[PDB]
Image (cartoon, grey):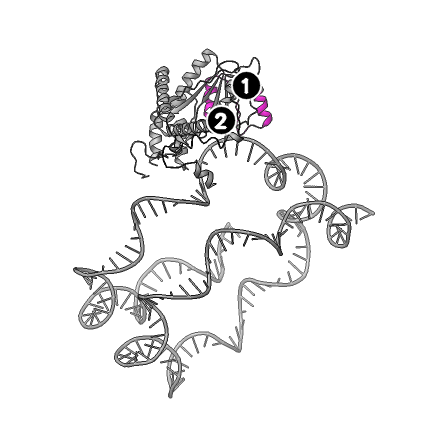
Amino acid sequence: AQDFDDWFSSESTEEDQDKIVKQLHTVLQPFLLRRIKSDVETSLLPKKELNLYVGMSSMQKKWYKKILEKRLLNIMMQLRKCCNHPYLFDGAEPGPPYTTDEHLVYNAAKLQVLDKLLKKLKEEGSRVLIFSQMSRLLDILEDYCYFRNYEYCRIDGSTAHEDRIQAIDDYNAPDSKKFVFLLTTRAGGLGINLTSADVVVLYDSDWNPQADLQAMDRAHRIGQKKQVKVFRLVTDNSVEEKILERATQKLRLDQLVIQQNRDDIDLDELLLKSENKTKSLNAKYETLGLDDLQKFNQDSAYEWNGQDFKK
DNA sequence: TCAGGATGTATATATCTGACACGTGCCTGGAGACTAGGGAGTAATCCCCTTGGCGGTTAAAACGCGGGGGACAGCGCGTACGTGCGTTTAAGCGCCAAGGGGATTACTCCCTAGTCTCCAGGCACGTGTCAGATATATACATCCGAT
């Protein structure tokens, strides 16, 4: 192990990072292969990443602060919950009695952006795939979809086989009244084919970039006819930014190592600002080096606006 | 049911003996230095535990049904307990005798512990293995529900 882990794995020596160890793919080219599907058939249209940076709402603000200064362990997971929808937390939503009115969208900034974009795509007429990462979050999405009078088909770690096949077939009927079609990002194996869809909204980003790559390939898989778009909601100035940063670290690591040597927020302004942020971070991480890329800076996310590790 | 008994149940009085208050001294808790080592805070490393989600195998668990036998209700009945009365008998209470047992109370010493100072050699840890305990199958002999 240590031989590979030290000879051209992580060091701290010199500009070796891109002068020698980077050039040392000659160890690998002998026995490894991959034929880039981007240009061997040239029949698919490329991808469309439209990361959206979103800020907390008041309920998110107070809940985020509550977790920062307190069953609740694994704080890094809880902050992801609060960044998605506070209704995941017990006793957050108003009630009882429990209703399903605009008090649902009224407390989740991602869900507000999602609702606006869902209306916009619906009037365009692009049936959409939602790839959440918590099945419990799919419950709130189901409730919202029903309250907005859309119909769906949910597949996750609960539905048995026959349910999965019949739901897929129902969505893929040649004249199917299926607008939204929920799933979980790492579920369904690989046989699930949804080329008939048009948009994949990555409600959450994943630690492993290739998990989402395979996920957002469920619509980009061979056979897809028209250019597709894949949104990725991000909670600006929160843990999700750290997660996206580390995921991009790993994605560029993969590319360098292998892929070379083959209220409303006025949606348009948020789109442009988030696109500028994406360009800025891409510029930040493009120029990194192997040993430099492997640091995993592990910036403690407990402190967010000034914290003291106290309750 | 009601009047006839039998039994607690309040009530006033006198007795007493046990709880309480009071002075002494002697012993222990408090004030006051002095000091050293236990513990709080810090840094580094590694293994375990969390939270949310997924996929799969496959025995247990849930459900329904039918039928028996165990439960619970009654019916005698014939004891074996109760209740009451008379009468011994023993518990308790005093008293006699002389000792030994024991618990302070106060010196003495011996000797046997604790303390320190090296220093080897017991033991815990990290390495192999191979022998015992598995799971498998099969033949058997051995209880259980109907004549």
Element marked by disc 2: loop
Q: Position of residue A180 (x, y in %)?
A: 49, 18
Question: Are dots 2 and 1 on a single chain?
Answer: yes
* Residue A159 drawn above or below residue A178: below
> What's the residue type where badge 2 is placed?
Thr
**Residue A109 seen in this snapshot:** yes
Report the disc number at residue A185: 2
Q: Which is more toward the observer, B122 or A14?
A: A14
Looking at the figure, which quarter contains the C terminus of chain A? top left
Q: Earlier in the sequence, mark 2 or mark 1?
A: 2
Tell me: A306 left or right of A182: left
Residue A191 position in % (x across, y down)? 57, 24
Q: Chain of mark 2?
A: A
Q: Residues within 10 Å of mark 2 (few under 14, many from 20)?
A: many
Residue drawn 36% across and 27% down? A60
Marks 2 and 1, Cα distance to the nearest angstrom? 19 Å
Asked if residue A144 lies in the magenta stretch, the reply is yes
- Which range is magenta? A140-168
Question: Residue B141 at x, y = what percent?
Answer: 77, 54
Q: Chain letter for mark 1, please.
A: A
Q: Which residue is mark 1?
A: A222
Percent of width and height locating residue A149: 48, 17
Report whether residue A106 is seen: no
Q: Which corner quadrant of the image does residue A249 belong to?
A: top left
